Image 1 (cartoon, rainbow, N blue to C red):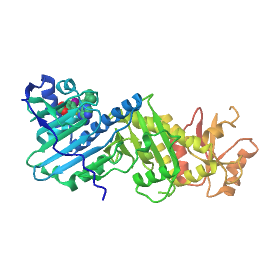
Image 2 (cartoon, rainbow, N blue to C red; image 1 turned 45 degrees about the horizontal axis):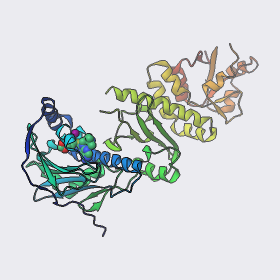
Image 3 (tube, helix red, strand yellow; image 1 turned 45 degrees about the vertical axis):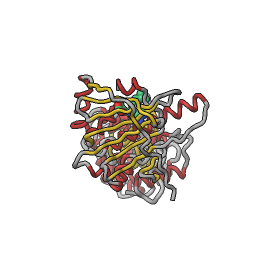
Length: 432
Ligand SMILES: CC(C)NCCCn1c(Sc2cc3c(cc2I)OCO3)nc2c(N)ncnc21
């Protein structure tokens, strides 16, 4: 068995610790984080991992920048049921003495579950001394020079009396696989490797290719088919977004990460209700019921444009897509309030036309681009094609030289009825 242990008692303090009042901001902040900020107390494990990752990254960066060799870059967790402790060490960039004295606020979440926190840290900088940092989370911490400290940071948590659960390996394992499956550096628990998954949404879209997208699709959608559609969307311009969206090839939710770190597996609010058929992940740093709105919209127009290009890249596959998911588009159109929201989604609708061969579809805008200036969009629900063609109501439009849209289902017609008007033109039935 591949048992990797890097965690042991090498640290010793020769002198005495100097005592140290928190600054008036930090006392209140610590209590806010430890007693209010988070709703689930397990997330401390999450936060401490995040920090660890960060440390490691800038270490890595730094070294690769200076152009020197890379050491072991790992994150280790150790549980101890009888000392009743949980420990997290990283071999990343450490903390200088000033960095410890002065100030990664997620760290303080540790005091949500601990009644004493014990830290050993040593900067990666050349000729850096190790230091010990101690605190009961009141208003007093202690600082002392320590020896036998490895480069990086070791955080030892002495759990509260009824928080002993986080000294159990099974519990901690569950928490880890829950929030930290996609950690960017190798993570071990009690000697055993945990994370195997690659946060492929952080990648460059050009560097990810099919088998990866399939693996991840099956992961987040918990499915066995393949995605029929794939949109890898990165942006920094409006807000920060690293997202992947899949449309299942089976005919009939998105996870919210930030930090390559899970926040909610069921982010139903991140996409509009009519795009609930979409699978995948949204990763955004601008995420602490308002900005989620901002993001939800941003994703909505992004996805709409996506499906439009999909139409104009492969109209037959998109035709099938409209047959399998048009339900959601009609629902979303009727559901919308502001008009051109309705029209935006309406750009995804595909219907048969009198000026098109029976079987072929077009959109409203396509229709309009052949609509001779002069003002109205004509449609008609018949049971089938040839019945619409032989409707007197249409045969009044045949030699009147006008194109007419053909619906074959009541929900389509109700949709166009609700829509009322689309871009500088109203939708009228030829039975009016
Ligand atoms: C390098 C440092 C300036 N980055 C700021 C975040 C501080 N920090 C943190 S959060 C933190 C941790 C503390 C602390 C204050 C913070 I904020 O006092 C006792 O230990 N974790 C780090 C880690 N594993 N490696 C390197 N730095 C860490």
